């Protein structure tokens, strides 16, 4: 009954869903493994992939109201809605896995914070599961409640998150002697020259680092699916998606450069650590600033840009603000994904063909909701909650999001290559060969990363294709 | 004007084209690398792939006369003729690469024979190219001339090839003391126990050996494209294809068992070699028969089931007969492939869209032929003849034949999955799900073998798809 346009919904949703856990937690590890000159390239490559997918989905949105259906005909016009259904089923399930990953990251960071606090629970690798289950139940309860409620919560969460980023940037400008043994040094050219070259610590590669990081540059299509409840589509969707992509890539580049220019991979965090910086050889550049963070490569030293996942949290002043920003990012991304997934389930499977969990009128929560599709995505998310540490989950995020984006790009290209009398796109900058390039790049990147996993996920989406086109 | 049915064309052509160079040359190396218990498994797996492809093409053949076209509509009825064109272009080019491989194998074996003879040419890795070019020009001269000519020559070639196999089998039953240091021992249980276990010599794996061997179990679909000039299709094609597949699989299994039960991996071929067989430890089973072929694992010894590619040629009596059989197999397979490829070019590209090499009336040969498609396949074949030793060519054979078979299986599946009102199969044993299984198995086997090469060939066939559906 209430409608919103061109700024709040699309822009805030895309820009908060794109700002997931990787921005504030794993980005320090990313710049630790791959150097600045390579982390920026990873950022640019992920930006290229996601912006090609955004141009792909802009052509879908800019199309007219196709009478065939607003669920699968738009995605696949030249060919049958079968790829539309397969893409919807894979992408919504990928969104469920994404909310699972985001809330796992939230659980991990809150567990780390409470471990740094007075006391902790039984196990750091088991309490994460319990707290994640509790908070995903909380999100499930809050999602069904209200429509403008979560809009206001989302805008205030964005305000808090942006204030946290500004706080971190302000902290970078302030070199504090209070933590000298910590990696933070305060814009020293020694920290830049040393960090400019990639240094893979134990077993990671350039593409493996990209594989871990990619979940960060994904999830704009979530805003796409709020088009059902959006006032003026076909302009708002492309405008908001492109602007959110630009701003998130800019902020990622800036924060990556800043974090790479303020700390080093190896730091022997300890008060007793000699920060004298005697005139020794010390070929490693870490000694240039002072004796702090010198020569801990023998055994695994304390932390700093390579062990402490909260390096950027510690570098900023008023650490509560940084932690609040992390919570805001994780919760907002999780809420957006958990809204997006079952809504796509209902939109592209409006017949409720396979399952009937509820009566499609009542539901679970304070007030009955005629959704009946939240429970399956919640169950899948909880099933992946039963595993922790967030490390093994990201492989599933990257493969499935890349598969969905590649399928979307290939479908939109095929709609623009075949005759497709009902295609008629109206977007100014949309090109068919650019979408072909994006789809091919997605496929190549997927198969380079864990080729057997890529083959398995293609076989899975193919089996989903036969399932959807056989049951129909 | 002349028509033949149910025996000669389909049966002889499939059985002669399936019996390529690998039967008489590379099979000894195959059983050398992979043991009997795995060489028979490789034989059975390749048989399963090719018989699933034969069932796939039987459904195509058993279909009625589709008015859409006898070129691409039959292959792709549910979906557009675009996959039909892409499959035709990839499969005919694969046939051209196959005739190149067959003729270069003929060149290699004749070069080896003449090297064993009095004198040889300049280089053993350069004269092969010259002799291969000369004989492929001879194939051009013989292919265009006559229709019953090559039929009678093909019958004679099959007879001489079967006689050569019989001669080899009779030689296996005859243990000759004339070559004791040679690997041949004459059905000794020690030779069986040692050979039953796999032993990959330098760098090969189980799938790499299968990759090398697979060209042997390919090429039946050549006879399929003889359906244009074949008398009574839709019965003769499946009957002959299945019967030839069964016969060639039985012969492959028998010859593999025989070669694995008559020789050993290591043999120090030398008259001065002590064949005394003193009562020593000699944990290797080679010493069990006698002192011959004992302990040459330090340096690379002479030959025998691991170095001599002509091990089965040497084991049989009247080595001229074995060499004649090798020439018969190579020449027959090359002639069949070189007939099949440009005929497919003309059949599935009857518009002569891209190139016009000739006037479509004259040609190259003793008499003018309105084909005009032989020259491009010859150019590709000679270009691949410009390299030698045929070792890197087989990777190209396996990937392309597997891609063509997988595409055919997927097309016939989707024709039986979608509505496809013009599909209507009539074959009794044709099943859609076994075709799915065959297509998936082809894809998996492709991607396990040199995953980047598999991805590249899929990208190439996809680009061919855009080309054919864009120029049309």
Image: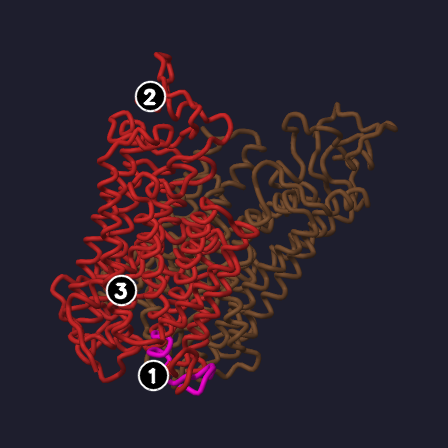
Chain colours: A red, B brown
Q: Residues within 10 Å of mark 1 (few under 14, many from 20)?
A: few
Q: Point out residue A345 in the picture as x, y percentages from the top left corner.
A: 38, 75
Q: Tell me the tag on residue A154.
A: 3
The numbered disc on residue A88 is none
Chain to which mark 1 belongs: B
Q: Measuring 39% from the left and 49% from the top, which residue is drawn there?
A: A211
- Magenta stretch prevailing secondary structure: loop
Residue depth check, mark 2 versus mark 1: number of the one nearer the observer: 2
Q: Mark 2 — on which chain does it sit? A: A
* Rendered-image quadrant of the C terminus of chain A: bottom left
Of B203 and B127, nearer the camera is: B203
Is residue B366 visible in the rendered structure shown here? no
Q: Does the residue at mark 2 contact the one at mark 1 (Cβ under 8 Å)?
A: no
* Relative to B152, A269 lies left or right: left
- The answer to whether residue B280 is above or below residue B142 is above
Callout 3: few (<14), some (14-19), or many (20+) C-alpha neighbours within 10 Å? many
Magenta part of the chain: A343-360
**Above or below — where is A152 with respect to A371?**
above
Cβ atoms at labels 3 and 1 below 8 Å apart: no
The residues bearing labels 3 and 2 have C-alpha atoms spaced at a distance of 44 Å
| B256 horizontally vs A344: left or right | right
Nearer the observer, B446 or A39:
A39
Examine the structure image and report whether residue A350 is included in the region drawn in magenta. Answer: yes
Residue, disc 2: A290
Check residue A344 for magenta coloring. Answer: yes
Say whether residue A308 is visible. yes
* Marker count (numbered): 3
Q: Secondary structure at mark 3?
A: helix
């Amino acid at each position: 009954v209430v409608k919103f346009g061109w700024i709040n919904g699309v822009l805030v949703r895309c820009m908060l869903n794109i700002w997931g856990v990787m921005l504030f937690i794993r980005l320090s590890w990313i710049v630790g493994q791959a150097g600045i000159g390579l982390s920026v390239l990873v950022i640019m490559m992920a930006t290229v992939v996601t912006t090609i997918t955004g141009l792909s989905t802009s052509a879908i949105a800019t199309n007219g109201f196709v009478r065939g259906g607003g669920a699968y005909y738009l995605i696949s016009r030249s060919l049958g809605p079968e790829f539309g259904g397969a893409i919807g089923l894979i992408f919504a399930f990928a969104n469920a896995v994404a909310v699972a990953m985001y809330v796992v990251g939230f659980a991990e960071t809150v567990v780390e914070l409470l471990k740094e606090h007075s006391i902790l629970m039984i196990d750091e690798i088991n309490d994460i599961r319990i707290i994640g289950a509790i908070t995903v139940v909380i999100l499930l309860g809050i999602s069904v409640a209200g429509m403008e409620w979560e809009a206001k919560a989302q805008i205030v969460l964005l305000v808090i998150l942006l204030l946290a980023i500004g706080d971190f940037v302000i902290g970078t400008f302030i070199p504090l002697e209070s933590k000298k043994p910590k990696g933070f040094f305060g814009y020293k050219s020694e920290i830049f020259n040393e960090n400019f070259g990639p240094d893979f610590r134990e077993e990671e590669t350039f593409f493996s680092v990209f594989e871990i990081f990619f979940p960060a540059a994904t999830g704009i299509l979530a805003g796409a699916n709020i088009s059902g409840d959006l006032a003026d589509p076909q302009s708002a969707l492309p405008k908001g998606t492109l602007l959110a992509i630009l701003i998130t890539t800019l902020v990622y580049v800036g924060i990556a450069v800043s974090v790479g220019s303020c700390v080093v991979r190896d730091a022997t965090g300890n008060v007793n650590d000699t920060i004298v910086t005697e005139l020794t050889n010390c070929t490693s550049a870490a000694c240039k600033l002072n004796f702090d963070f010198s020569s801990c490569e023998s055994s695994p030293c304390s932390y700093g840009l390579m062990n402490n996942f909260q390096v950027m949290s510690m570098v900023s002043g008023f650490t509560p603000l940084i932690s609040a920003g992390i919570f805001s990012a994780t919760l907002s991304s999780a809420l957006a994904s958990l809204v997006s997934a079952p809504k796509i389930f209902q939109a592209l499977c409006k017949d409720n063909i396979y399952p009937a969990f509820q009566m499609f009128a009542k539901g679970y929560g304070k007030n009955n909701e005629p959704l009946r599709g939240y429970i399956l995505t919640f169950l899948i998310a909880l099933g992946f909650i039963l595993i922790a540490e967030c490390n093994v989950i990201a492989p599933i995020i990257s493969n499935f999001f890349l598969a969905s984006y590649a399928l979307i790009n290939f479908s939109v290209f095929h709609a623009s290559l075949a005759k497709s009398p009902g295609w008629r796109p109206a977007f100014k900058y949309y090109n068919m060969w650019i979408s072909l390039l994006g789809a091919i790049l997605c496929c190549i990147v997927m198969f380079v990363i864990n080729w057997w996993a890529a083959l398995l996920t293609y076989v899975i989406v193919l089996g989903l294709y036969i399932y959807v086109t056989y049951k129909k």
